Amino acid sequence: DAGGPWARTFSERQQISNAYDQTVSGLEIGLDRGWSASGGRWYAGGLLGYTYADRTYPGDGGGKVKGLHVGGYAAYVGDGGYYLDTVLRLGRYDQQYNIAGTDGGRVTADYRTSGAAWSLEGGRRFELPNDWFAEPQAEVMLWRTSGKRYRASNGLRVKVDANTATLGRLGLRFGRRIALAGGNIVQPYARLGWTQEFKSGRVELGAGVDAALGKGHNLYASYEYAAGDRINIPWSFHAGYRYSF
Amino acid sequence: DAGGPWARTFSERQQISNAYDQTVSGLEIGLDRGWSASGGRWYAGGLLGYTYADRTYPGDGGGKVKGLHVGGYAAYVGDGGYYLDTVLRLGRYDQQYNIAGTDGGRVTADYRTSGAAWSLEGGRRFELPNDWFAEPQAEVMLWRTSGKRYRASNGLRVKVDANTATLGRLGLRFGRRIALAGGNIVQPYARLGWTQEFKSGRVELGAGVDAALGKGHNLYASYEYAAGDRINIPWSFHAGYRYSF
């Protein structure tokens, strides 16, 4: 690979508990160029995304969330098996919140907001007999959302909070690299992960397949499930395509 | 008078400054019974009211406010010329606020609230040559509004504040008691007043006429204008009728 275009979709249902359930869906599109740094292989490039979060509070109601974002990233891939990516995302959001107060009271909201998310991720691939691999991975993630706050004089006050959150993520995948008649590479794996959040914890189990289908094509699909403290993700799908061009 | 039914309407435009203009309109209805306490004349009774406040913020929008209230009151009237009334009002309100954030953001609100207002008022009538009178008056007023506050998790916060406010009021009226052929009493006066508010200042000028029209009827009408710090009341009308039954 000397770089290429790529597209990735995704969709994850969160059941976050006391309590709201949201469905987060997205689409990224992107391009990088690659080069030979001796000992490794370097990748730099950028991306464009949509993102849609659809939420629900119990009796009440909840928000919808739409957003464009752009981003830039570098990736290294070592001969020895080390990888790391860092990625910077800048986003603008549009939320239409819609609540109820069980007393009968109905508050409506509608506003734009700004986000950034920076993440850094690395890990190593240890090959094992019969083309099975082992792959520990670490991902720290930082992001900020912007605030807003106004006020109808002699009465009402509305504040949107600028929350700002760190993530750590630990995980391991086991798979087999398996070569089909022709040139194809189907490469299944199953994945175990832990992740937590300080925002100014949970375990995840999933499985995927990444195929290299001869003539520059690449397909990835994975499923993920997570249970945790606040958190509960009955399903989380990612599908991705890349052209080695 | 041994008591009777009464109705009073009113409407006052406030231009309160940095900035919102509101029009406050109302209707009270009420009844009291009267008796002879030697040296004076005592009045006790109750009332029912509607009240409508229609507000406006600059570019933005603003609220509407509807409310039922009930109340109870006593009044004393001395032979010597001293009067005092105390009145307790209990109310429930319905506000539909509607704002804009000049950034494009639109927040909507809709809720019920509770109020009470207790006031105590007194003063003396000094008669002067040719049936002109002088009448200093003092009015302290206490009232509380109730609060409300909810919150869309991991985002938005809405607070309505329970404000709670004292008023002092100083004023003087000069008029002439004037007796028409038959039995009628037209009694004009002009009125100067000061009032301020600690809420956890301004001067007022107006004029009225109170008629006793033979056979138990009573009519009052007044106009009032006020200018002050925060405050500016280009107009404030009160009309009232009472049947001496």
Image (cartoon, coloured by chain):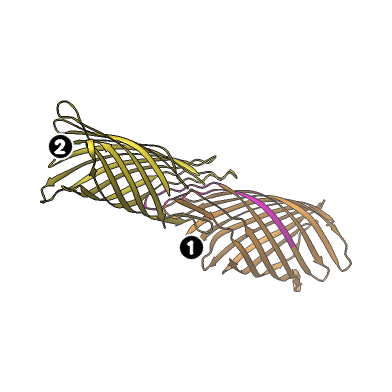
Chain colours: A yellow, B orange
- With B175 as the anchor, is A104 left or right in this view? left
Q: Which residue is mark 2?
A: A244
Instruction: Identify which residue is drawn at 72% across, 62% down.
Output: B187
Q: What span is in magenta?
A: B86-110
Task: Out of B224 and A5, give the one closest to the viewer.
Answer: A5
Task: Out of A168 and B87, give the one closest to the viewer.
Answer: A168
Hey, which residue is sitting farthest top in the picture?
A181
In the rendered image, residue A126, in percent from the top left (x then y), is placed at 24, 45
In the rendered image, residue B198, in percent from the top left (x then y), is placed at 59, 68
Decide if residue A116 is in sight here: no
Q: Residues within 10 Å of mark 2 (few under 14, many from 20)?
A: some
In the rendered image, residue A96, in percent from the top left (x then y), is placed at 42, 43
Instruction: Identify which residue is drawn at 18% across, 39% down.
Output: A5
Q: Is residue B1 above or below residue A128?
A: below
Q: Which residue is mark 1?
A: B17
Task: Out of A19 and B164, give the one closest to the viewer.
Answer: A19
In the rendered image, residue A39, in percent from the top left (x then y), is placed at 12, 51
Discs 2 and 1 lie in a common subunit: no
- With A56 as the anchor, is A93 left or right in this view? left
Q: How many marks?
A: 2
Question: What element does badge 2 sit on?
Answer: loop
Is residue A100 highlighted in magenta?
A: no
Q: Chain of mark 2?
A: A
Hey, which residue is sitting farthest front in the picture?
A129
In which quadrant of the rendered image does the N terminus of chain A lie? top left
Residue B160 in which image quadrant: bottom right
Residue type, mark 2 in image: Ser
Residue type, mark 1 in image: Ser
Instruction: Identify which residue is drawn at 75% across, 51% down.
Output: B30
Is residue B97 highlighted in magenta?
A: yes
